[PDB]
Length: 97
Ligand code: NA
Picture 1 (tube, rainbow, N blue to C red):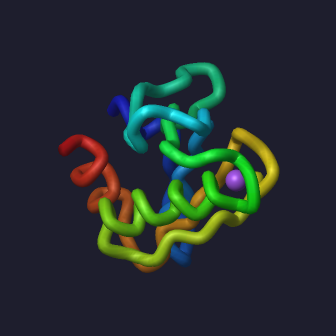
Picture 2 (cartoon, rainbow, N blue to C red; picture 1 turned 90 degrees about the horizontal axis):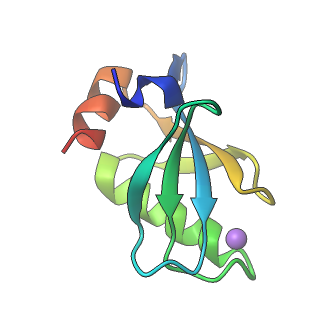
């Protein structure tokens, strides 16, 4: 039930709602924001030239084994990621690893 506040399953896959902090020591999940319903993700990339977006997508593509696109928030800290062709059950399993 922990990550469920940050996810919903559409016909296309799962929209994972995140809030990023760039120039981190490691790209990783550090928590959840219970009011915003977003996973707190640290991203080990500078927020310039799209590099934090790229690193974020790379991390989740590797985690989920699925294409990940930013559907909203390309220029925001609050980003919605579509994990294409995956179920919510599969995403929860991988986030809980
Ligand atoms: Na960026």
